[PDB]
Structure formats: C-alpha cells, structure tokens
Amino acid sequence: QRGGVRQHLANDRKKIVNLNIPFFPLDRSIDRADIQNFREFGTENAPATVDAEVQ
Amino acid sequence: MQNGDFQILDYTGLISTMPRVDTLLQSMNLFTEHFGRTTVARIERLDDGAGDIKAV
C-alpha cells in the first residue's frame, strides 16, 4: 500500500569445492630362465630372443 | 633339431660302425680260377714208377 513500509531484496549464493587425484602404477620384469631353451613361435628350429619378449 | 615342441637342441652328427672281414688267403694268390661252360668238370691222373732187377 502507498505510503507504507517498503520491500527488501536478498542476495546470491556461493560455493567452493576441493578434489584429489588417484594414481595407477604398472610393472613387470624379465629373466633369463624364460629365453634360454625356448623356441620362438612362428619359426622352426630357431632360437628365442630377449628382444621379442620385451616388445 | 627340436626337443619336444617348445625347446631346441644341439645336433652333433652321426656315428657308424662296420664289422671285420678277413682277407688273408686272398692275399696269398694260392688259387687259380677257370671259367667253363657247364656244371661238370673232368680230371685225369697218371702214375708211374720203377721195379726190381734180380740176378740171372
């Protein structure tokens, strides 16, 4: 109503957040015992090799 | 070579052996060889000698 009390307005809202991150390791090893007397697949009467298993 | 299916080998060749045979007589040339025509052979022999001479 005219001549009476006024009206008022509010304000906004704010928020903040924090986060972390995970980690993913992976590893495998090699040894002589697996490449000495074994025969490479796909070939015949040929010896295995260390490089092939690394790849 | 290949041991089993997944393994390899070292190949060292072959070894051979034969039995003995003796050739002593053939080395002596002790026999004479004749070549005929049929399966039958003939041989002839002759003997001779001497005798006594009594007094007369």
Image (spheres, grey):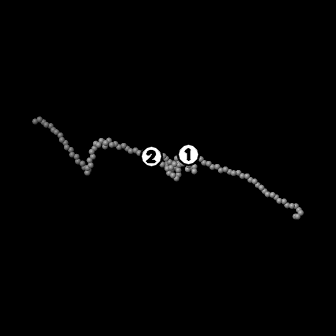
Indicate the amino acid at tag 2: Gly
Real-space CA distance between mark 2 and mark 1, rounded to the nearest whole angstrom = 29 Å
Is disc 1 surrounded by few (<14), some (14 to 19) or many (20+) residues within 10 Å? few
Q: Quadrant of residue B23?
A: top left
Q: Position of residue A2 (x, y in %)?
A: 88, 64
Q: Where is residue B5 in the image (x, y as percent from the top left)?
A: 51, 50
Q: Where is residue B11 in the image (x, y as percent from the top left)?
A: 47, 46
A3 in relation to A41, above or below:
below
Residue on which disc 2 sits: B13
> Residue visible at 77% across and 55% down?
A14
* Residue A23 visible within the image: yes
Between B56 and B34, the residue placed more toward the observer is: B34
Q: Are marks 2 and 1 in contact (CB under 8 Å)?
A: no
Residue on which disc 1 sits: A32
Give the side of residue A1 with respect to residue B20, left or right. Answer: right
SS for dot 2: loop
